[PDB]
């Protein structure tokens, strides 16, 4: 109830504050208010309004599944970052509560969040390498060493989250952002996150999700391995082989391990198989798989292939 009391001073205002304060306010989001977490983004006279205090790039172009992620610039500081626009009516408290206060090089830094009208604007570091999703499309598919390298980094992000009892909930290439030189990958977008003790991408769904079973951190591991397949093949699993209601096929069919490219090294194939066990209790954890994937990268000679480089044909 004292938490409830402190939230009142925050309501109706945009302030520069700390992560815990943003999390507490976000709990009330189920007309301009919020907390900005970096001095690079500054409120003006209790406000932070779109096209007034911050502006989106040029004519508005987006990234993300819904074209909801934009480049933006603080008009006062000149600082450039990314904004994810979320509809207030659909906003999930966990999108901010699960990630406010996190600190890991494997998770994209949260810069703040501001409600304005029917919008929750979530601000974060702009990673100028773009998304791993964009990279797969741009390059066709990724060589084995680079795919293992990014899976490894995603799994390190997952270790950090799972230890803290946070389920990401939608691990996929679109949700992995890259530094300008491609050397650093970080998890982003906690829209589907859950605090342990709402559907992610269907192709990446674990059998226990589709079957309505109780879910734990292992769901992120299955999804990360569907992302691995996406990286190697240039397409999602279940894209070929099945052409109807997809959720049923995930439940009834063997894991999509037949999509592992034959040319992959044995430990790569082994790692993907352990992450794609249908029963969660049999599936590798984030730590186990991260060690296996790190070893697999070493087994193919470490990271050698070019950042960008040459278009490789999708399967």
Image: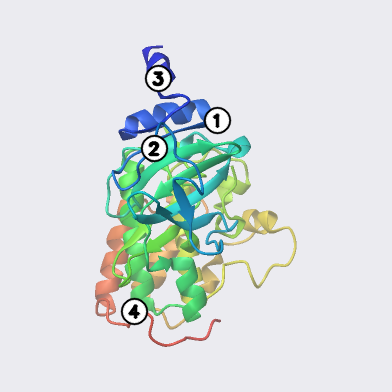
Q: Secondary structure at mark 4?
A: loop
Between circles 2 and 3, the one closer to the viewer is: 2
Circle 1 crowding by C-alpha within 10 Å: few under 14, some 14–19, many from 20 = few
Of the image marks 2 and 3, the number of the one nearer the N terminus: 3
Residue 265: % across, % down:
36, 78
Q: CA distance from mark 4 to mark 2?
A: 41 Å
Q: What residue lies at 67% left-to-right and 54% top-to-bottom?
A: 247
Which quadrant would residue 44 be assigned to in this image? top left
Furthest residue in direction top, as rendered? 1
The residue wearing badge 3 is 9
Q: Residues within 10 Å of mark 4 (few under 14, many from 20)?
A: some
- Among numbered discs 4 and 1, the one appearing first in the sequence: 1
Instruction: Work out whether mark 1 precedes mark 3 in sequence or the reverse, and give the earlier one.
Output: 3
Tell me how far mark 2 sits from mark 3, CA to CA.
17 Å
Local SS, label 2: loop
In the rendering, which numbered label is found on residue 31?
1
Residue 118 versus residue 210: which sits nearer the camera?
118
**Residue 36 at what x, y percent from top left?**
36, 39
Label 4 to label 1: alpha-carbon separation: 44 Å
Q: Secondary structure at mark 1?
A: loop
Residue lying at 49% horizontally and 67% vertically, measured from the top left: 133
In the rendered structure, which disc, 4 or 3, sits on the residue that comes first in sequence?
Answer: 3
Give the quarter of the image for residue 96: top left
Where is residue 184 shown, x and y percent of the image? 30, 64
Mark 2 = which residue? 44
Q: Is residue 48 above or below residue 295?
A: above
Q: Nearer the viewer, mark 4 or mark 1?
A: 1
Q: What residue is shown with label 4?
A: 307
**Measuring 49% from the left and 70% from the top, which residue is drawn there?**
134
């Amino acid at each position: 109830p004292v938490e409830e009391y402190l939230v009142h001073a925050l309501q109706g205002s945009v302030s520069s504050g700390q992560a815990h304060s943003l999390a507490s306010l976000a709990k009330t989001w189920s007309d301009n208010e919020g907390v900005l977490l970096t001095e690079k983004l500054k409120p003006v006279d209790y406000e932070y309004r779109e096209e007034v205090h911050w502006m989106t790039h040029q004519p508005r172009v987006g990234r993300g599944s819904f074209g909801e992620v934009h480049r933006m610039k603080d008009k006062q500081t000149g600082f450039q970052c990314a904004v994810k626009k979320v509809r207030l009516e659909v906003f999930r408290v966990e999108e901010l509560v699960a990630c406010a206060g996190l600190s890991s090089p494997r998770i994209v830094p949260l810069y703040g969040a501001v409600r304005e009208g029917p919008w929750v604007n979530i601000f974060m570091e702009l990673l100028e390498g773009g998304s791993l999703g964009q990279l797969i499309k741009q390059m066709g598919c990724l060589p084995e060493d680079r795919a293992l390298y990014y899976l490894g980094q995603a799994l390190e992000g997952l270790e950090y989250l799972h230890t803290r009892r946070i389920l990401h909930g939608d691990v996929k290439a679109d949700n992995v952002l890259l530094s300008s030189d491609g050397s650093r990958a970080a998890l982003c977008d906690f829209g589907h996150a859950l605090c342990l003790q709402i559907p992610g991408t269907e192709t990446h769904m674990a059998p226990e999700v589709v079957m309505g079973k109780p879910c734990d951190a292992k769901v992120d591991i299955w999804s990360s391995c569907c992302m691995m397949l996406h990286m190697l093949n240039g397409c999602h699993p279940w894209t070929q082989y099945f052409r109807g209601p997809l959720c049923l096929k995930i439940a009834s069919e063997p894991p999509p391990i037949r999509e592992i490219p034959p040319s992959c090294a044995p430990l790569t194939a082994q790692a993907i198989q352990e992450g794609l066990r249908k029963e969660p209790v049999h599936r590798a954890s984030a730590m186990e798989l991260r060690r296996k994937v790190g070893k697999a990268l070493q087994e193919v000679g470490g990271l050698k292939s070019p950042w960008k480089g040459e278009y490789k044909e999708p399967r």
